[PDB]
Image: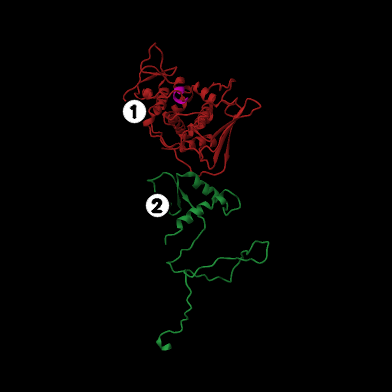
Chain colours: A green, B red
Amino acid sequence: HKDSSMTWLKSYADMIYDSVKNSNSTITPEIRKLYLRMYNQYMRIFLPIEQYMLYDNTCWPFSEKITLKINVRLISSRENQPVLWKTPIDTENLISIVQPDEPINKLNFTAIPSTMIRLNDNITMYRAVKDM
Amino acid sequence: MTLTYWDKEKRMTLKQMIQQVAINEQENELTHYVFTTPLSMPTFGKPMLGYVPLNEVATSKFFSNVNDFDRDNQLAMAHFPDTTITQAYNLTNSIKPGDTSLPDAEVAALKWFWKFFTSINLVRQPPMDNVMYWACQFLSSGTSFLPLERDVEIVFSGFKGSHICMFSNLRQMNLSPILCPYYDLITNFKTTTEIRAYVDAHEELKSLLTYLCLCTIVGLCDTFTETRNMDTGEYVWKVRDVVSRNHTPAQNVEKFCYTIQNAKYMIQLVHVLLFPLTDNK
């Protein structure tokens, strides 16, 4: 399903300096030290706690049992078939509609064409021939 | 007694060692390196016989970045265990005017050391980030050799600033009948514990090699700046983040325009004189 995957990688690699250099971040906060190390060393290879058990001795004498992964679990789409969402009713928290200074919000928005995903008006009226 | 550190004004190397500041910073570089047997790599079948000096023109020619005249095997008279040394520390194979040689242990130690220094560009010395790590390790934690867990900056204040003259009154400084008993201790198979006791006690060589590792890092770093407090003759000069932003020697011709093979000399130096402090092979 090759894709914006690499572009997404590069974007998220960029969207951390706005977090690891400035304050007010999800750095929580030690990821700073770990990420600064990883960015400043170039020599060590950082292996999660599993792989280190296998990388024994005969390579780069520069490594470390890294841990404390960043928590971002992203889903993967199936084949070209589309995706459906089942917007919920149960929750514990809320999200804001238009900025906390104003009433009614209006998202004047574009539209899709008809040469894209079409519109069928054919109403399926029959199963097997008996129903006729 | 070691040398009056000159500035146009005398010194005793002790004021000039308590003159500085070594202050740490953020970004713990949890990157504890490991030592290494210092790769003596001695060999060649073409020596220079005669009276080769071994103290002052020796140390100057080798570590003062003076003429890079190929500075080769001339020390190769450090193999051949039957050579001798005359008290002025002239290494020879024929003591001419009835002059006397030193006792044995002294000879063994001195030959050991210069033997380690013989033939650089055939030595396979380790990359320099690690040697910077060990140097700052020593001069920060002391002779205990705990890993850094941080990073360090060095700053000097008030010198009639002449770091070139620092390197100079190095050029004029003797060391052999200062570090002889130390390598003597390492020759007859003592152990880390007692030699650490020794270096703690005597403290004449402690100050010396503190200064020496300091000078080599300030000569091989590149995060270096200087300034003169223009109200008096007093330079403050700093070197910032010594171990993270340095991977090769320097060429900024504003601080100390340092060549190459003498730089690998210097790293061999700090390697081979910090060797006996640390743990096993």
Q: Residues within 10 Å of mark 2 (few under 14, many from 20)?
A: few
Residue farthest toward the left in the current orientation of the protein: B45
The image's mark for residue B43 is: 1
Q: Residue at x 43, y 88 (%)?
A: A131
Q: Is residue B102 left or right of residue A12?
A: left
**Nearer to me, B40 or B180:** B40
**Nearer to me, B20 or A91:** A91
Residue farthest toward the top in the current orientation of the protein: B97
Element type at mark 1 = loop
Q: Can the viewer see residue B198?
A: no
The image's mark for residue B76 is: none
- Above-or-below relation of B103 to B138: above
Q: Residue at x 52, y 47 (%)?
A: A36
Q: What is the magenta range? A: B59-64
Element type at mark 2 = loop
Quarter of the figure with residue B111: top left
In the rendered image, which residue does mark 2 sit on? A54
**Nearer to me, A8 or B183:** A8
Q: Residues within 10 Å of mark 1 (few under 14, many from 20)?
A: some
Q: Residue at x 44, y 25 (%)?
A: B62
- Looking at the picture, how far across and down is residue B173, in whole percent? 50, 22
Q: CA distance from mark 2 to mark 1?
A: 40 Å
